[PDB]
Image: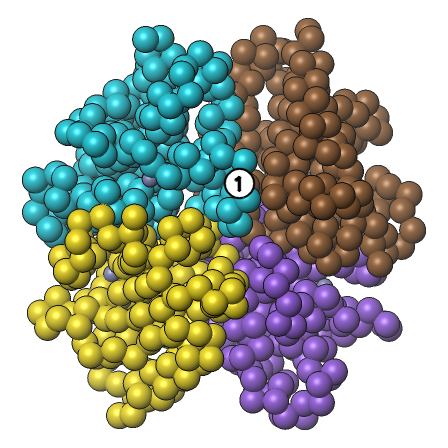
Chain colours: A brown, B purple, C yellow, D cyan
Amino acid sequence: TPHYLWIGCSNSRVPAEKLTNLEPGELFVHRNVANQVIHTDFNCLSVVQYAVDVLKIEHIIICGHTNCGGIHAAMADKDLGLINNWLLHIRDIWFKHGHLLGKLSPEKRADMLTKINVAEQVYNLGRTSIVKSAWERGQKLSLHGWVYDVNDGFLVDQGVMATSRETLEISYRNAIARLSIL
Amino acid sequence: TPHYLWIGCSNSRVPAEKLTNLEPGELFVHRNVANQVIHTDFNCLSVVQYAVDVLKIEHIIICGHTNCGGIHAAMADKDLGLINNWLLHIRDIWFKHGHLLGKLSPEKRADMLTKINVAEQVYNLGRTSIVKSAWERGQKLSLHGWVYDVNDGFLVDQGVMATSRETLEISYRNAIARLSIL
Amino acid sequence: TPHYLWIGCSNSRVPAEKLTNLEPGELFVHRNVANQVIHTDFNCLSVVQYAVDVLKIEHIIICGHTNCGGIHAAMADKDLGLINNWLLHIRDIWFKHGHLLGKLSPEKRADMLTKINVAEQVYNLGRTSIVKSAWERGQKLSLHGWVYDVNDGFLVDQGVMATSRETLEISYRNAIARLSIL
Amino acid sequence: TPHYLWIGCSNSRVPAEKLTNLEPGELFVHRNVANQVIHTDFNCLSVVQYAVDVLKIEHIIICGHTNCGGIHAAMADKDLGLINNWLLHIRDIWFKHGHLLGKLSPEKRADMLTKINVAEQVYNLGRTSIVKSAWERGQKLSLHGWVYDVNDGFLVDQGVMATSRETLEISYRNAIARLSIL
Ligand SMILES: [Zn+2]
Ligand SMILES: [Zn+2]
Ligand SMILES: [Zn+2]
Ligand SMILES: [Zn+2]
């Protein structure tokens, strides 16, 4: 059985098995554009549920990555059909952290939004009743939100780790605080 | 750019870049429970849309797999939270083809539904207006439905394979016809 | 508090309060294009849940109606953006009952698909774990699927009533049987 | 044809054709819990899309309402199944404006979030590529955000009102600004 859920980007360069060292078959995997955990996405939350409730997975990694098409698209004006809907959530995050991102060098803005996004998705994941329950019923379950850079390993935006709803609060607000340091 | 969208199951026992000899960086990936393409799932369809429109991918592989817990769960009566919703589509598929599955021995059954599912999902994928437009505007785009025999090689063909909406009808209906007659 | 959930079409001529005689405030209302209950629609199922679990509603009416734009669109070839995704579920129903509908007079085909649709949505609704639970925990909860005709009151396609998962099976397969009589 | 899409809450205490003096047959309606327009909700957005593209509606009224159980539930910690997912968007809105709501007395709070929600939802509705395209192609389309005071008249203005994407930014941001400053 798998012990890890990897929520990553569909992006071809970011596959769990090569960013991780996990034994073959340890990785339950969900990938979607910009590694989102939208509150009302049955797709992702079904994986999270199946992971958490069927497989009793104890680690969920939301891995985002740099130079992520989703993030760029989120920030772009292009009509990408359904992607617009999907990335609107990311734009929400973008707008929510507009103070911070406005400051940043336009190019780095994408990479910040990637870091932030992961934070937000973990925050989303961790506020899921799926995860909140796993915890509430004392199941061990750690959420991690990382950002993998194509040319750099993990951005050490480590930030995003929750093992409880409370640690989520701290980690999340903490990560957001860290990222705001500039 | 990658050349394949791989829509597969979140089941680790199916790592795409490994089980195809394809390069890492060549598989745009979406995985979800029982590798579904639900008409109204922005998650998957965003991946597809990103794949088809942004990456201009030419091959969408929906790859199911045997001993897929998704498929098993669909056939269980067990309340698996959000997953029940997700898997009710698979149960539609089960019941849609209940007669075929009725005829089958109750283990063959799972692996049949697994194959059928791939077909249904290809069919869904191909009636996507995303995929349909790609085709309508001459975008070379083939849909492929495979099942990875988890305990084995790899059924590099469920027969379902569409390079157009019409080839979709044929391939799919033929696949179903076939799978209904061994 | 409301005692009835009305899942109807967004169609302006089909508002619950005027097709029903219910006291002001008795109607929890969800309407969407072609009054669907898609397994993985958080929107509708949230209303169903809220209805069933918060409001302890004891009656869910999926009211469809004749000359329903959704149904027509379902059957039509038009690109209606997100509507295509949404009505693809209805097309599924259409294709699932293609034998029956193929027979029918093209015009009546739409009205049959409307009757069928309601059956299917109730079937969907009733296989929801929300409803299955209400029942499993002995809560009184009756699903009704009707089809209101603009010029005729209810099509007496009465069919579609479930007060239990078993009655759903019967009512549903029964309704489908009735509709197949031609 | 109807001239208004009414996006409201499933709460019966809000019947649209009645509370507006509008004709029955003039309100295309979507209702859901806390009258949300989630970027990735095909349900609502299909209604909107049908409204905007098929019915060529010129007014989308998102109408929230006071003592909205949706809003209350969002603010409760209670596990309400699928509804938690649905309401996590409202909780984002709550927390997004936590400071404002922090400042408020904990009852004003609900009715504030109710108003804020309408604004957020209008904002979401207006960043819909559905609505954005209608505008981009000169379709006369105004978005309106109202709150029906359930115990009263009707706040025929939350201030949020957009006839374009730019008027969307202004109206929305202004609404938020306002609601943050009484
Ligand atoms: Zn990416
Ligand atoms: Zn599987
Ligand atoms: Zn209709
Ligand atoms: Zn309400």
- x, y percent for residue B158: 68, 75
Nearer to us in this view, B88 or D47:
B88
Label 1 crowding class (10 Å Cα cut-off): few <14, some 14-19, many 20+?
A: few
Position above or below: C86 against B181: above
The amino acid sitting under disc 1 is: Lys
- x, y percent for residue A139: 77, 46
Furthest residue in direction front, as rendered: C138
Quarter of the rendered structure image containing ligand 2:
bottom right
The residue at 33%/76% (across/down) is C160
How many labels were placed on the picture? 1
Position above or below: D95 against A56: above
**In which quadrant is the C terminus of chain A drawn?**
top right
Nearer to us in this view, B98 or A134:
A134
- x, y percent for residue B30: 66, 51
Position above or below: A14 against C76: above
Q: Is residue A118 visible?
A: no
The residue at 51%/29% (across/down) is D92
Nearer to us in this view, A78 or B136:
A78
**Secondary structure category for the residue under label 1:** loop
Where residue D167 sits, quadrant-wise, is top left
Q: Is residue B169 visible?
A: yes
**In which quadrant is the N terminus of chain A drawn?**
bottom right
The residue at 53%/49% (across/down) is D81
The residue at 75%/24% (across/down) is A159
Which residue lies under the disc numbered 1? D78
> Is A139 left, or right, of B109 in this rendering?
right
Where residue B157 sits, quadrant-wise, is bottom right
- x, y percent for residue D161: 25, 25
